[PDB]
Amino acid sequence: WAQGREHVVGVLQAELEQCQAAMKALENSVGGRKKLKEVMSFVDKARKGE
Amino acid sequence: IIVEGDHPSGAGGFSAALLARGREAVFLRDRADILSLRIQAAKSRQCKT
Image (cartoon, rainbow over all chains, first blue to last red; front, top):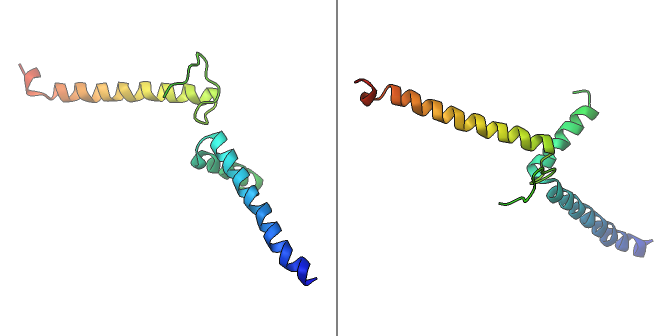
């Protein structure tokens, strides 16, 4: 259990890093990070009641 | 920058209707500046005569 505990951190964080990169990757594709954050603001808003 | 399209769909992250909206926006900008510049010309001393 202790061994699985030590390994899960390095693995899980490596999954997170590829996740953030894929996000940046989507950022460049859409255009500006600022623009993508705008569309994200529109979707979050539409998802909330705003 | 160069784009090479007669009809660009997404360039610099912008949709086909978004490029139209910016073009019109630059037309309005150059129109506005020219209008300001002509108002300044009307208040110029050289239009007094």
